[PDB]
Length: 114
Length: 114
Length: 114
Image (tube, chains in turn purple, orange, brown):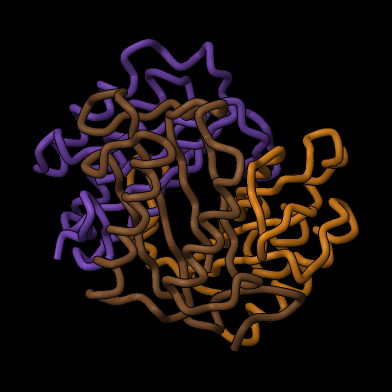
């Protein structure tokens, strides 16, 4: 899985340990081994949500499987919870694009997962 | 809807008011309320388009519906127009990826739009 | 085609000529003219792969066609090779998301490619 968070929250407001926390919580929620989880946080961004520049986040979660209606609801509760708690971003100012990737469409280690 | 623009144009060349203009015009084009429109501009990027580095933009528009042949032509005219007028980027150095998202695959406010 | 590389490797480690090399190699690999190839490198990112902050890369290749099982294995060998050689990133710390775009869903030059 690959989880990307883009936010206008400044770098100094991203707490130490945030990437590890994301990694651990995602391994668990998705059921995948931690070794396959990639995380990326991009602070200080020029962005708006609903016209407003109050704290917000634009995110994505790509994964080979483990994407679906109920699963995505559960990821959203988790991720929004973490963004609220750690970055002080309101959940209603978060968007997460979920994408179910075909194994043939993910390159890794000189090949793909197909 | 979520609109992202990645560009090599420098931050000081992004005019005041640009995120609001993008929010307004995308609300109108998509028919969605401005409160649901998110915009993100990423200047000063290391990028090339067709081998050169004159001003260019790599963008995406993710929307739940309102994506299709004619609509996307219309979004491209609008968005290329705005990038040309405000960031001085030639339309033939703009790429926009359009993604029609299923409501179950967009997280927001601790759940999805399903 | 559009190729994007997000990496924690620092900007100074990205060699001069890397965008042109990517452009040329992708033109050859995809068979598309270099005028249609866009490349974007984002260094100094806050990211982790497998919980580790050792060098890694999160990438994507969007193309109208020329995406598939065998092709993507080949692109992954090529791309991982280049990231290892030029950025010193281990291939098993690289993810590449491949997306086969419909021509109607790519905006360019005030219209789409449809």
